[PDB]
Image (tube, rainbow, N blue to C red):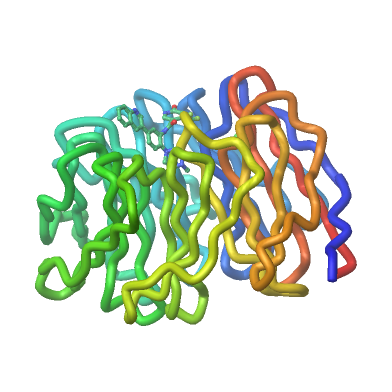
Amino acid sequence: VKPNYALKFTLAGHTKAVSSVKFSPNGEWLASSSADKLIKIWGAYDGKFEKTISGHKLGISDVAWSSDSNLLVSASDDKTLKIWDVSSGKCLKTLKGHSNYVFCCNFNPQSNLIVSGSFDESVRIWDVKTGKCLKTLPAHSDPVSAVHFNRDGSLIVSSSYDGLCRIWDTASGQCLKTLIDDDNPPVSFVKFSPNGKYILAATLDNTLKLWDYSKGKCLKTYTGHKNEKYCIFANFSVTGGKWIVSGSEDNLVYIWNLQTKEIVQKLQGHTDVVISTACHPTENIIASAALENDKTIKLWKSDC
Ligand SMILES: CN1CCN(c2ccc(-c3cnc4ccccc4c3)cc2NC(=O)c2c[nH]c(=O)cc2C(F)(F)F)CC1
Ligand SMILES: [Cl-]
């Protein structure tokens, strides 16, 4: 009925705000990105520092893993994405085309494509092998905060400060759906559920919503956290009980019961805004990352 996440490790090494944490799909690693221009890799289960990957000329907003856990893509204020071979540390490609800061990135499940979102208000779809931009979608009328492929990679969901969530046909680039409820505050985060049936979206009015995107309807609302300024990443936790996990501008990690919308746990320990959370793919493990006054990542574990 409630999880019991408790602090296991604190991962220190970044010298500026940590922007994003992601578990590799094989569960072995955690990748982090930071305003210090670095990506760091850490052991998912022991928190042990593994390696630093360098190359971007300015801060990094996001990182994401290929399905086989061998590659990473990073999104940077230097207006590029980079594709990295994690084992070698090599920069395989630099993806150039956005006209301003790149805020978000994801591989498709096949991992032959990358999707990015930018301050330039576009969503771009890239070929992984060539590094070429395949499509530029004039997706929004304000900065794009998140981009995510669905389960089979046929759809992309995007969120923007224009107050909309939009769903795109990956093959054609056509907009298939615009989601909007009874108001349009900036949408700061969106992703598909693991089964691809729902979309979780955050807005800068301290709210998370669960949407049925086939039906175009909001099913659940989660509140009690603080989120009016930063684009804070949230997740579905599915390995034990079914939770919603998010960071918060009061420095806590919030966990909600997905069905009942009740807050079930608030994880204390960070000293600044928790801007990113991630949920381990097979174990009940959460990673959280915090901003400039904290500079650390924390790994929490629960029995359920
Ligand atoms: C995993 N998340 C991290 C936050 N993302 C993001 C999203 C949006 C913006 C942003 C930034 N500026 C904006 C100005 C006007 C209107 C909208 C704006 C939106 C800016 C960001 N990125 C940052 O806040 C950021 C950028 N560059 C960094 O070096 C470090 C960070 C961060 F604060 F650590 F996360 C998305 C991915
Ligand atoms: Cl190193």
Please, is residue 166 above or below residue 13 in the view? below
Spot occupied by residue 135 in the image (x, y as percentages of width and height): 11, 59
Say whether residue 44 is left or right of residue 201.
right
Q: Quadrant of the N terminus?
A: bottom right
- What residue appears at the point 14 percent right and 55 percent down from the top-left corner? 133
Classify 278 as above or below 192. Answer: above
Q: Quadrant of residue 153?
A: bottom left
Looking at the image, the residue that sits furthest to the front is: 182
- Residue 149: give x, y in percent of width and height: 35, 68
Is 47 or 233 nearer to us in this picture? 233
- Residue 295, relative to residue 245: is it above or below? above
Q: Is residue 50 visible?
A: yes
Q: Quadrant of ligand 1?
A: top left
Q: Quick check: can you spot residue 91?
A: no
The image quarter containing residue 276 is: top right
* Number of on-image labels: 0
Residue drawn at (41%, 75%), measured in percent from left and top? 212
Q: Quadrant of the C terminus?
A: bottom right
Residue 74, image x and y in percent?
A: 40, 44
Q: Residue 84: where, in percent of width, then height?
A: 41, 50
Q: Residue at x 84, y 55 (%)?
A: 5
